[PDB]
Amino acid sequence: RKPVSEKIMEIKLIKGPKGLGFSIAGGVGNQHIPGDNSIYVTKIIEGGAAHKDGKLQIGDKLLAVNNVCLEEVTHEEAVTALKNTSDFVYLKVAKPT
Amino acid sequence: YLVTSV
């Protein structure tokens, strides 16, 4: 019932041989946290693109991929967005604060 | 339930 603040940040990632180097959970019908439909980052691979860049963190909400908004979408819709990317990907995330 | 690595 108290206010919850987030910091909104854009992160540009360049894929490596193993892709972006993180995992997502969440989505409408696939809640990562009860009552929350957000897409969440849940894993970051050591040595991967997200790791080396150093901005993305476990616990971050994934708000968008490129021009595709991921607020209140299904896990499948989030995956579809991430699948349809080139070697350069712009993520919009919300970090706890 | 569903988790995806990318």
Image: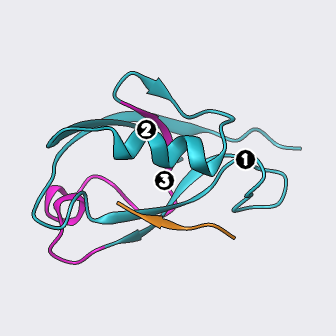
Chain colours: A cyan, B orange
Identify which amino acid the numbered label 3 is placed on. Asp
Confirm or deny contact between disc 2 and disc 3 (CB under 8 A).
no
User: In the displayed structure, does residue A80 sit left or right of residue A90?
Assistant: right
Name the image quarter holding residue A84: top left
The range drawn in magenta is: A45-65
Q: Residue at x 76, y 50 (%)?
A: A36
Mark 1 crowd level (few <14, some 14–19, many ≥20, 10 Å Cα): many
Q: What SS does tag 3 mark?
A: loop
Pick whichever, A29 or A31, lies toward us: A29
Residue A54 seen in the current view: yes
Q: Secondary structure at mark 2?
A: helix
Amino acid type shown at disc 2: Ala
State the image coordinates of residue A27 (x, y, percent, origin top left).
67, 49
Q: What number is the disc on residue A60?
A: 3
Residue at image point 38% right, 60% down = A57
Query: Residue B4's mark?
Result: none
Callout 3: chain:
A
Residue A2 percent across, percent down from the top left: 82, 43
Is A94 left or right of A53, judged from the image as shown?
right
Quickly name the residue at label 1: A37
Residue bearing mark 2: A81
Residue sitting farthest toward the right: A1
